[PDB]
Image (cartoon, rainbow over all chains, first blue to last red; front, side):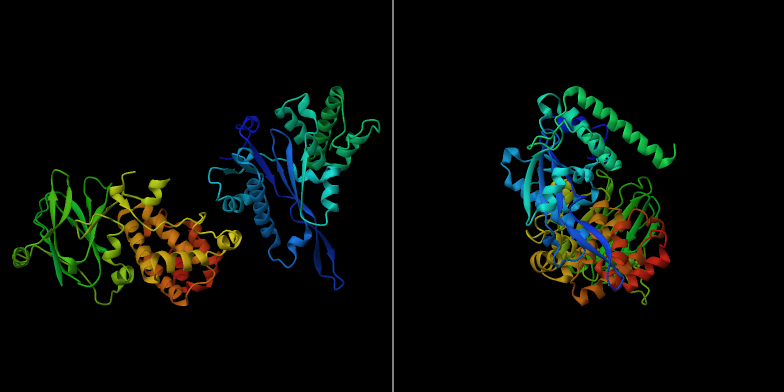
Length: 237
Length: 300
């Protein structure tokens, strides 16, 4: 069924599963027309599909052309997301195909379910957790590749950089969600924290700086502090 | 006018015929129902005074034979049986009448209700759902399951309704995933109307059969089937105008006939809010909308 705090360690067993986040698929700006009405201009979006065990990210870029001459665009983004996740699954070797797929938003259930009809033994699951994958686009290199594209384009990353070489999935995923939680809550601050020290650099093949172990601890501590600060400010606690 | 005699009434029971029904007391001398309109299907059903669980009955059509009712004490229920001896049957029928131990099918001539409920119900179609082809009449009860339910146990006792699944390959043409699923016209018109049911009138017959089975037996699979058949039409952007208008009439009479205190299990909140207010056919069930609002404003 649904994924929550009870069945949380299931993400890290050896059953291949993916997360699908669609929040960044249909992205717009809002502006005023010459006649003063309101009008939306769309920009390149991205499907965020992620293997929480291995860090493998399947970042499907969604070009603005896909909207050209289309109605009920927000509804359509769901079906497109589902189309493109199903095409990803079909392109993978049977043994690489996932046993399950977790949509971070319950609206995607029907579209994906329809689209995955040919894989009846692939379970589509909602989640009760409140994952922060909408802030995927606060990661500089992901936003850059999205915003540069001239055509539908698939790009592969490992969103854990090389961390697994020294830590576990569970921990990797926790770091990942924490860093994204902060970037969501106050991006300017979260980003200050990650880049303050010009001497800790981001490898060309990596998304995050090459912190030593000790430095990761500092950083998690600073990220945690930021997130508590922002909540007190939100509710006057 | 046809008659259905009863051998005997050993046990206290509430007997129903079509939408009528009568209390009969243990070893009351009851011997049958007379003046039954030749022309439609009928259904005679039972609820024992001792087990309000398991209501049960038999669908039939007098033009197919002479049927009577006999209590079987091994199985403990009223069984429908057919007499093959033409002469021997009229003899029991005329004696009980002249002893007047029979109740008259009590039809007001203004009332078109049973026909409106059974307009499209044919026996031949019924016996392809309650397969038991050594008998010309069909037995249904509260606890019988359908074929879709068996999928998600004993197949002899199956209700072989037509299987409708909105999230199936059948219903969803590859490439038209979003289209076919927001707009079930394909599924309705080509798969189900032209392919499986052949015409509108069979479709309706099954829909109406489903309803009556749920109403008279609280057959929970039958309720589900009826709402699925409604749902498919109401989720179809392109429907023949004759079917819409007939559907508005068919439901109207269904809502009208339902016991008022059962509106909670037999009416699926989602499907009806979709038909009447959300779906393509919101504007097209004027009569069903209106009865629904004035009778069951709560559920909406």
